[PDB]
Each structure stands twice: as structure tokens, then as C-alpha cells.
Length: 114
DNA sequence: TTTTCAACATATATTAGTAATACTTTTTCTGAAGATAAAATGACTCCATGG
Image 1 (tube, rainbow, N blue to C red):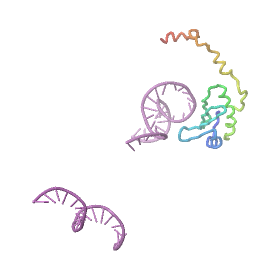
Image 2: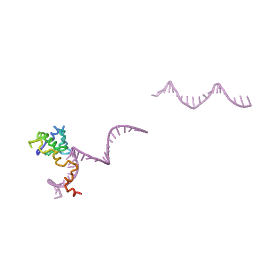
Image 3: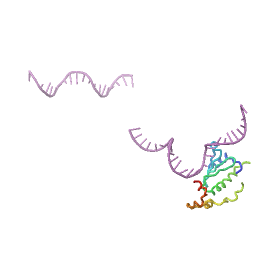
Image 4: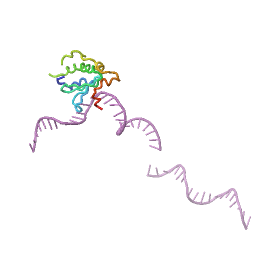
């Protein structure tokens, strides 16, 4: 997010959905059930997000929680559209789903990988 | 020489999927004086044979 984040009050507020342990690991652990993703948090605002099977769920959680990020700040802005890029199944379809299509997608380098 | 850097690296935590092994647990599951008595003491007697 390119701005600092105060975690000590973050979990102290959201620790129902969050956890913060100074000893083990520097940042904060966040638990979101809706959708179900764990959000790994730091001081600088660099946020690592996983525990998701779906690309859309990422921007879902990141989106919904970003107002919590703007909530806790010390002294971008516009989400634009919630979903911009094509869905996941589009890029899954960009590759042949048929189990028997291989030699067509064979890189020809695997012919050299023997 | 010493100090600051740096730097290298490596855990550290998440979320998975396995799969397999090893490893701890847990949960069965058994292998003070004067009555009261108990017994040893002893006499009594039934009852044995024999001259």
C-alpha cells in the first residue's frame, strides 16, 4: 500500500479476525472467512495474500479490507472496478483442457529433456 | 585493530496439497487393670482283657 500501518491497534480492534504476535514473525496475521483467506501484514504496508483457490477472491478480500487500511493510517485511493482482468477459467481455457492434447503443446524442448 | 557495514544465509508462518514414517500422547486393560478364653493338666470313670 506504500504507506505505514499500525498493527498494535489493528488486531486490538480486528483481532477477532486478526492476530499479532511480536515474538514469532514481525507482521500481523489476519483471518478472513468471507471469502476465506489469511492476510499477512507488515509495518511498511507490503501485504502478502494467499490461502485462496480463486483469483477473484484475492481482489475481493484486498478490496474489502483496504478500507480498514485507510482506517488505520498516520499523518491507491480509488478501487476503480472491483474486477478488471479476465477470470481464472478464461486462462484455464487458454490452455487445452483435453487430457490427450500434449504433443501439440509439447515445447519440443522436452523432446530434448530426455 | 576495531568498528560499522554488509552480506549471506537461514529460519521464521501461511496454504496448501500428498504419503509415509516416526512419535508421542491418550485410553483401555490386567497381575493403664480386670473380665474372657484356650489350652495344657489332670483326675474319673467306662470299658478292654486275663489268672
